[PDB]
Length: 51
Length: 50
Length: 94
Length: 64
Image 1 (cartoon, helix red, strand yellow):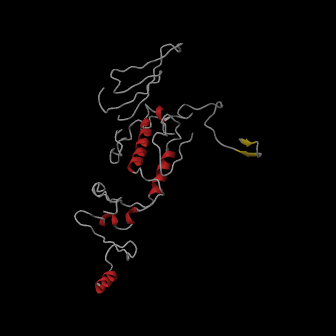
Image 2: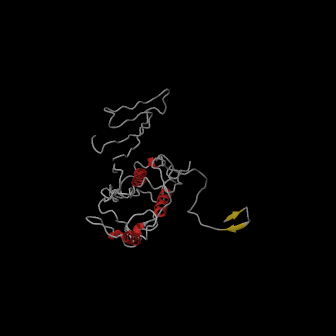
Image 3: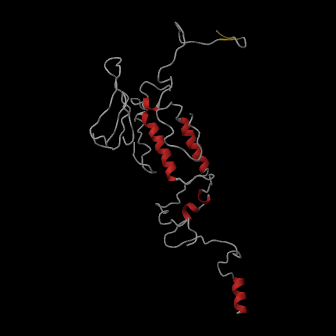
């Protein structure tokens, strides 16, 4: 049940079975990658498509 | 391939080394040249030749 | 990746959909340098011509004889061809 | 530092491959916009006929 403390409104949503939660920086592939980093990656989405 | 230059990394055995420096060498540098530090950045000139 | 600098130099299918992604920058750079060197004089406005937009893509031929004779008007300025009136007056005057 | 702003004239060495990934579809859109603006009317511009410009290099000298 999410509440916005800037406009005082209530809303709900679903989460993927969270035992915990926190904030952290993402992996290098999502922390800002570089063209000359995908030296081993190819267009055959080797287990990575959501980019 | 032609023009493509892939970057190579050299991780020294010890986690750290003071006053360390690398001077990359390759026989007949006319085919390619590399230097600096652990980061190589190999450049390719021809389409064949090991 | 090709080592050419001009058009019609690399198969669009050369990436294979399997090549490594680190070559994309080299492909974009190649494309840009090709577009730059194939039209180095394009600096004025776009100046769209599209080859007359209608038919000149095939009719514009010059192999052993020219065609599409110009339909210019009179050349009272910059006297060139022998305009009929002028030559007639000159001949009748002598 | 943002180098993804170019029109009618591009630069091949500005991308500086060792750069963030935002450089990409942005440059592709730029190339497409430049190509469209330069010639926004294209069906089949085949007015070359196997490099006729070489023998027909008389376009710049309309005197002779």
